[PDB]
Amino acid sequence: PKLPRGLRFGADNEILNDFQELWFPDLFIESSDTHPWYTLKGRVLNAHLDDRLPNVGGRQVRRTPHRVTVPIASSGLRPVTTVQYDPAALSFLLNARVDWDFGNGDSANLVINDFLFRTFAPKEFDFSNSLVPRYTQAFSAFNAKYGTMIGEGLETIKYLGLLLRRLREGYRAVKRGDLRALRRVIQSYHNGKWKPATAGNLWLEFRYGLMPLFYDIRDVMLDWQNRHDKIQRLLRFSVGHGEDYVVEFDNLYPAVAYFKLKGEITLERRHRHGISYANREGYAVFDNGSLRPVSDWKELATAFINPHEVAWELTPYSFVVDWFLNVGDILAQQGQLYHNIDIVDGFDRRDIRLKSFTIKGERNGRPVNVSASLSAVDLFYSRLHTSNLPFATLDLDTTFSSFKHVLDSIFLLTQRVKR
Amino acid sequence: MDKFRVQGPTKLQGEVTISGAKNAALPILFAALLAEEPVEIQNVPKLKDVDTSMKLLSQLGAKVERNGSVHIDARDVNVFCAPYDLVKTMRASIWALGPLVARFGQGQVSLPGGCTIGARPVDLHISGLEQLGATIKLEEGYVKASVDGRLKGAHIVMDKVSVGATVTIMCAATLAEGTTIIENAAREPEIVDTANFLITLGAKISGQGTDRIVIEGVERLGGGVYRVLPDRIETGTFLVAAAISRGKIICRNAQPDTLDAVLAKLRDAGADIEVGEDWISLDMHGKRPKAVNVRTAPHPAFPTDMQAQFTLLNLVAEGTGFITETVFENRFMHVPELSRMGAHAEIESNTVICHGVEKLSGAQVMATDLRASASLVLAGCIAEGTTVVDRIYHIDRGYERIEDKLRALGANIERVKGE
């Protein structure tokens, strides 16, 4: 239907996000081996040769489509993509180089190229008693560690609204024509009480008189971007802890099948769980036309600052009033990130890495020097999505509820500014 | 991909006819390359591995035909190069290297694959030819072997007991000059049934079921008539589905002498087992099975060919049972498939810990092994839920018309087309 993966129609040709596919995908069956052929270089039994010997087969890997299209909201995070990787076994390429020098007949120096094996992968392990205390300490110490960083954002948004109230009174003095309620505001920024100039032009004292005011409002707009984007980054508590498990393997007799290879691969089992907070009525619709990047916020701060412009004479009534219309559109989109905060996300990642390894090698009961280097190709990775939460006493809904009333008081002030 | 869909739960009451063998019929087809007289083989079911060997011998130059009985007359073989799509399909195709150097003079056998059961212990297959009189050489995976005259006779000192090591030495020492004594052989029932076919031809091999067998070397033999005995695994597999459903099944055409220690442990659990010569009865009287702790060992004393067959029975029992696997330490695929249904287990080193639960729920499973494919189909006849088995092409490799035998007993099973 003219759509890639993860898209669905909505209103007037508007793309959405299907919930029956991202959370419950449909895995397939793949039967294809990675390296079905390899070579065995070197000299064996005093006879150098290089052929093309194949290996084994039967590799069933079930994967899921990886999607990174549209997110869930504007200026948010990527949705929970179900990435399932369940291979048939654990295959690792081993570029070994076993050689022995004993007597005159038992002398060889063969180089093993691309050697893999198939064993077992115990993927049945849970850690439901280690990630639960980690969430209690993070929520109990949130009011003590971040108790001062959040308070700075509340006093910053309230201080910006006070400057917008005095700026609105300056526009009303042009239509009315009162000169007493215009020259006294300019003297409030300086130390004493003086006037830089006195003329009959109402727009001459409005530009130069508000020069220190433009430098203070610009610093608030640049600081609000850092005090708002850092809060959304703290909603990614994806911590976890795992243990160790070794894997034993024997009966390895490659090439001439006269020397025994064995070892002990020490895997690294990891299991972490992530939790995010978003709006319960924000991920329903998503439009790319109204998505304004962060570059539009920095442009409005330098609108009044211009060393050479002709906007003061080409209909000035359609320039200062339109500036407040773009500010209300930004506050209307950011206000949805604090209205009714409900737990809607939550992913669980479980992957297996690889650490050190101690491999050996014998030949009919004889110590043989081993100098190989084990690699890692086929591993293990899992990424699902849940919809439950054990403990949910203290939430961020009551804390972020006070920030909604502050943003709504500023949006209603810009709508009352008429021409 | 074709898949099944068994519902229920129903009851399994009735009789079932045991078909031919599988592991015992493969060495018989390879022994006809040395005989210059047409032999007669009976009791051969239509399987995937059986039909694969028919096309392999047809490309070599031996005209084969069958309709009611197998009559292979291999005496006009001219092509020595074997294809690659037929050797990698199965696993026991490497046993043909014996007769392709005893009577002819050359042969090219590639590396087989088959099902994922381990690391392919082919170390004893190469050492078993140098002591007899062969040349160690290979090119592009084709194991070449050329030697003038028959193979010599010498005492072979083995180290470990394998599966294909006994068949390789036995099938390559019949017409060879000299007396060869196999030390520490395999006493599995597949060797006893295979040795009976050589006695009819004219071989002087006495002492079946013993680690030390004295093989007498002869010059040339001829043809013979011998009926293949039914499989012992198929008889014991149907007894597990009846014990978990609390019923009664009467078997026909079985070999009680091949399953001595298999039926000995089930008698103490509280089940009436009736012995005989052609019929084996078993009943549970509605009781609950128990758990046994018997270590895997070559026949007798619980053979290693009953791992996945008694895995589901130990889970539905009570207590704590463990089975120490020392042969197939890499075939651990039937454990993750049963854990999704609602069971818990743990594999420590080389011993699986089986607990004791009641019933499970049917879900989507995947069968990638041979013996692990029958345990997933019989579990759906008693569980509550839809059982979907992925990759069902392994069931037809050892069982012919499995959906038709279970239909008369009481199981709604149908075949769904795929590719």
Image: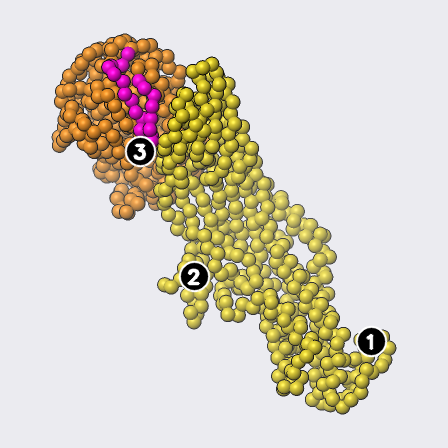
Give how far across and how far down residue A283 sits, in percent: 51, 62
Estimate the spatial distance between the alpha carbons at disc 3 and disc 1, rounded to whole Å.
91 Å
Residue A365 or B287: which is nearer the viewer?
A365
Q: Write down the residue under mark 2.
A: A7
Query: What secondary structure predominates along the stretch shown in magenta?
Result: loop
Identify the subunit bearing mark 2: A
User: Who is closer to the viewer here, B194 or A189?
Assistant: A189
Q: Which residues are magenta?
A: B134-152
Q: Which mark is residue A190?
A: 1
In the rendered image of this protein, does residue B231 appear above or below residue A236? Answer: above
Label 1 sits on a secondary structure element that is loop
* Horizontal and vertical percent position of residue B65: 14, 31
Q: Residue B86 lies in magenta, yes or no? A: no
Foreground: A242 or B166? Answer: B166
Determine the chain carrying the residue at label 1: A
Compared across the picture, whether B309 is left or right of B320 comes to left
Place of residue B388 in the rendered image (x, y in percent of width and height, measured from the top left)? 34, 44
- Residue identifier under label 3: B88
Circle 3 marks a residue in which chain? Answer: B
Look at the numbered disc 2 and give the secondary structure of its residue. Answer: loop
**Drawing shade for chain A:** yellow
Which quadrant does the C terminus of chain A fall into?
bottom right
